[PDB]
Image (tube, rainbow, N blue to C red; front, side, top):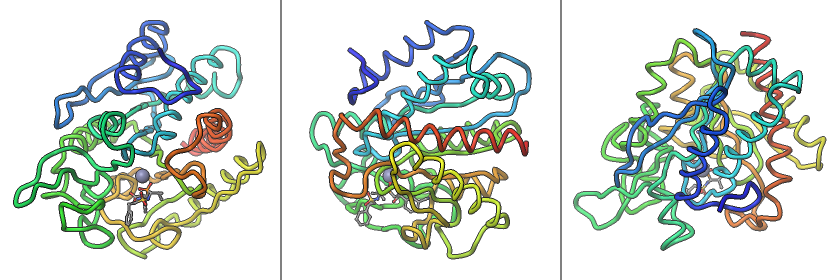
Amino acid sequence: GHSYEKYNNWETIEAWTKQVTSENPDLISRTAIGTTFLGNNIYLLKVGKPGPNKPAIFMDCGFHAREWISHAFCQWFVREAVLTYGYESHMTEFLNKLDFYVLPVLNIDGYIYTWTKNRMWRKTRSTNAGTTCIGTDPNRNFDAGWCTTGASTDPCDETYCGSAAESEKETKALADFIRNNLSSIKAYLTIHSYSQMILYPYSYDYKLPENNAELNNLAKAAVKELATLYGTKYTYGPGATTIYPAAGGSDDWAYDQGIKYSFTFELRDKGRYGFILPESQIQATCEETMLAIKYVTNYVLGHL
Ligand SMILES: CC(C)[C@H](NS(=O)(=O)CCc1ccccc1)P(=O)(O)C[C@H](C(=O)O)c1cccc(CN)c1
Ligand SMILES: [Zn+2]
């Protein structure tokens, strides 16, 4: 049984992806872009008014298994899109002019693991050689200054960068989809928790992005928009200095491919509850995050 105000297990999220597609068959289509190490289907939703060669915004949730408010947000976002499309000017224009690619859970194997054995698991669940330790950090597994800084070469560590860039089937699947659609994808948004930040490149080096000016200004505006609702305070900036260095991230990789609007969101809270954010806070967190996402969508649309 699914709720937008509770955390749902994978079986339920998987059924939800099929359910929401069947109820909105002319607004939403569903695809599997690959399978996890354990063989689960990695689903991607395409949301928008059907039309030839539209630009798109790409958003994923659930890179990291324990960051449950991330998964909850992609679901919240899709419902908001559907509920307001057709009679809210902004969202109606949004889905008229572009598509959203929503990947509700990337790291499905880990998510199941956090529901069944260890709530605090982070990584994938693939096997490693030379050690009994399991898993690779998906946000260390992309071809962006891979394993050069901010990652561990130790497979027992939480930031293990993997056997090689895109060693993980999940990261390969995501990377492969985006490569094929680099033409249409105009923005990349990846949702994490916690610590209340908006990050943009770079994380694999203290080097600043070409349009560092444009991105810093957009993030500043986004966090101001988000705080309007509940006063929630976000910080923002290039990844390496705003949080810490972390090579192999999907946002840096997205930006180096030609996606000049690439952001990582870190949602509530700032550590009081951390990854175990109370379900009573799901709605508030999602509502305010929507304001930032919509602000970014409006901008990308305008400068498209
Ligand atoms: C709480 C939140 C800040 C997460 N950090 S974490 O779970 O403590 C990372 C694991 C860890 C734990 C202890 C010591 C070293 C690493 P995150 O996992 O969502 C941060 C994210 C990452 O580490 O992949 C991150 C950090 C820096 C830059 C970017 C943008 N690519 C993204
Ligand atoms: Zn994370």
